[PDB]
C-alpha cells in the first residue's frame, strides 16, 4: 500500500530527543508499537516527526530503521532503530497553515503521540526543514 507513511512522535522532555539523536534509537507506547510495525513492513519508508510536549517546536524528523521486537520473552524492551534526517528545531509557526485531514483537519502541531499524518500534508511538513540550514 502507501509507499510512504508519516507519524508524529511526542517526547516528554528534550533530553530524550538528545539521547535518540545521538544513539539513533527510540521507543514508544504499546498502542503505537502495533501501528508502527504494520507501517514498517507495508510502507517503503516510515517517517517519524518529533516534538517535545508543550515545547512549541518540532525537534526534527527521522526515518524508522527497524521494527519493535516484542519477543514473548524495561530491559531495553521495545527499543527500535531510527535514522535522523534533520535534527534542527522547527517552530510551530512555520507549520500553522498545515492541517491534518486524518486528525479532524486540526493543525499538525496538535497531535497525540503516534498520530499518522495524511501523506500530502506529511510531505509538506518535511519540506519546511529545507528553509533551515
Image (cartoon, rainbow, N blue to C red):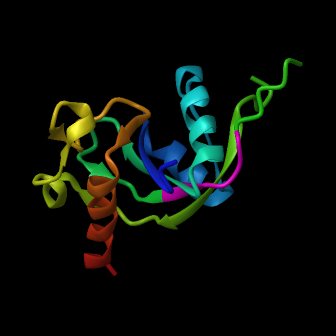
Point out residue 8 in the picture as x, y percentages from the top left corner: 39, 42
Q: Residue at x 57, y 31 (%)?
A: 28
Point out residue 35 in the picture as x, y percentages from the top left corner: 54, 31
Point out residue 76 in the picture as x, y percentages from the top left corner: 76, 32
Is 35 rendered above or below residue 19? above
Is 15 rendered above or below residue 120? above
Q: Classify residue 128 as left or right of residue 49.
A: left
Is 84 rendered above or below residue 106? below
Q: Residue at x 59, y 58 (%)?
A: 44
Q: Between 70 and 93, which is closer to the camera in this rendering? A: 70
Point out residue 85 in the picture as x, y percentages from the top left corner: 51, 67
Which residue is situated farthest in the left direction here?
A: 97
Q: Residue at x 33, y 35 (%)?
A: 53
Q: Between 68 and 16, which is closer to the camera in this rendering? A: 68
Q: Between 64 and 74, which is closer to the camera in this rendering? A: 64
Q: Is residue 48 visible?
A: no
Q: Give the image quarter of residue 23.
A: bottom right
Q: Quadrant of the C terminus?
A: bottom left
Is 23 rendered above or below residue 42? below
Q: Residue at x 84, y 25 (%)?
A: 71
Question: Residues in magenta?
Answer: 62-67
65 inside magenta stretch: yes
Q: Classify residue 117 as left or right of residue 62.
A: left
Q: Is residue 4 visible?
A: yes
Q: Give the image quarter of residue 80.
A: top right
Amino acid at each position: 500500500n502507501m509507499p510512504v507513511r508519516y507519524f508524529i512522535m511526542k517526547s516528554s522532555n528534550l533530553r530524550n530527543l538528545e539521547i535518540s539523536q545521538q544513539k539513533g534509537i527510540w521507543s514508544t507506547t504499546p498502542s503505537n508499537e502495533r501501528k508502527l510495525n504494520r507501517a514498517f513492513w507495508e510502507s517503503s519508508i516510515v517517517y517519524l516527526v518529533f516534538s517535545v510536549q508543550g515545547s512549541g517546536h518540532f525537534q526534527g524528523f527521522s526515518r524508522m530503521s527497524s521494527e519493535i521486537g516484542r519477543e514473548k520473552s524495561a530491559g531495553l524492551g521495545g527499543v527500535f532503530k531510527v535514522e535522523w534526517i534533520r535534527k534542527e528545531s522547527l517552530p510551530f509557526q512555520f507549520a500553522h497553515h498545515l492541517l491534518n485531514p486524518w486528525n479532524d483537519n486540526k493543525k499538525v502541531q496538535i497531535s497525540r503521540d503516534g498520530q499518522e499524518l495524511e501523506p500530502l500534508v506529511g510531505e509538506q511538513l518535511l519540506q519546511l526543514w529545507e528553509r533551515l540550514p
